[PDB]
Image (cartoon, helix red, strand yellow):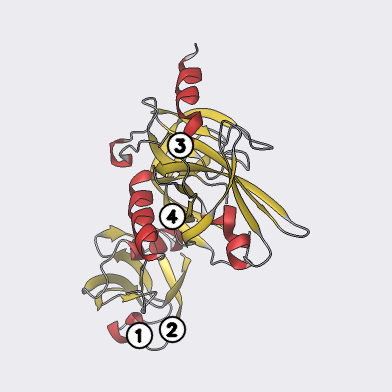
Amino acid sequence: AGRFTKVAAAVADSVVTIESVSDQEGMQGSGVIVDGRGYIVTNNHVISEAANNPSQFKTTVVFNDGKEVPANLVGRDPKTDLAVLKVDNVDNLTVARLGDSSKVRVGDEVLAVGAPLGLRSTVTQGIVSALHRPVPLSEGADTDTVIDAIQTDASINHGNSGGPLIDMDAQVIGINTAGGLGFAIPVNEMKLVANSLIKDGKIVHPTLGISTRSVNASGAQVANVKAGSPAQKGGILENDVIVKVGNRAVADSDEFVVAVRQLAIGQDAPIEVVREGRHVTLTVKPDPDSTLEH
């Protein structure tokens, strides 16, 4: 058997099709079994329209061996484009076994696996082309977002979106997202997001009340500060050029949004700013974006 033929055949039973149908709509994607009780990780845009209109959409999981089972949304995170589904009382699930994306290196051979039975399903091959790659994602009413992504030249498309990025040990190192190089959500962020979605149905991320644009002191240029925000109270002014957030240099608006999410909620953090030719450090305490779940 081929080298990638073996790795793909060993993870196929862990990748499923995710189908969502209404009176006049249809959207399909892939998912991966991360827990033996029936927990499936997919990306948030695969299910977004079903989550927004659940009274009309029917969500279904289809396994490798043909079986078709209804599924429920446990939780979802548009900020990391992730979601958790649950199938009930299905036995002998081949659980995917999860790697460590911090141990991933540029040049590592990978496979972006889509659901073996999906309509337009794909399985592509490439290498890791970049790590911690901030990438913007923009198909429903959710927020646009940015993620620190694993970048690969394995093609990511409708057919393998939501399925796993797999290393040569048949371990999951990421979740493919199509929302011509590819991008995956690293598996360590997926464990954190999925771990907290399973228990609480929600995660909470820090927020500053800032929206930026990319700057020739380059960085993220403050376009608007929300009233009452942490940026408000910390001293951020509009047209500030943010160059550091916490311990992360900020090259543009994409890295800014990613850098904000790595911060601690309720702890003081320095924002280093280029203001009218000067450098100014400001202290900002991030609020939780979901204060009732915080």
Which is nearer the N-term, disc 2 or disc 4? 4
Q: Which residue is mark 3?
A: 165
Which is nearer the N-term, disc 4 or disc 3? 4
State the CA–CA distance, disc 4 to disc 1: 25 Å
Query: Farthest bottom residue?
Result: 228
Can see residue 292?
A: yes
Q: Which residue is mark 1?
A: 232
Secondary element under disc 4, as helix, strand or loop, is strand
Query: Circle 1: is it few (<14), some (14-19), or many (20+) Cα within 10 Å?
Result: some
Task: From this view, report whether residue 273 is shown above or below residue 179.
Answer: below
Q: Quadrant of residue 268?
A: bottom left
Query: Circle 3: is it few (<14), some (14-19), or many (20+) Cα within 10 Å?
Result: many
Q: For the point 52% across and 40% down, which residue is it?
A: 182
Can see residue 219?
A: no
Task: From this view, report whether residue 10 is shown above or below residue 238.
Answer: above
Question: Is there CB contact under 8 Å for labels 2 and 4?
Answer: no
Question: Is there CB contact under 8 Å for labels 3 and 2?
Answer: no
Question: Is there CB contact under 8 Å for labels 1 and 2?
Answer: yes
Which is nearer the N-term, disc 4 or disc 1? 4
Question: Label 3 sits on what residue type?
Answer: Leu
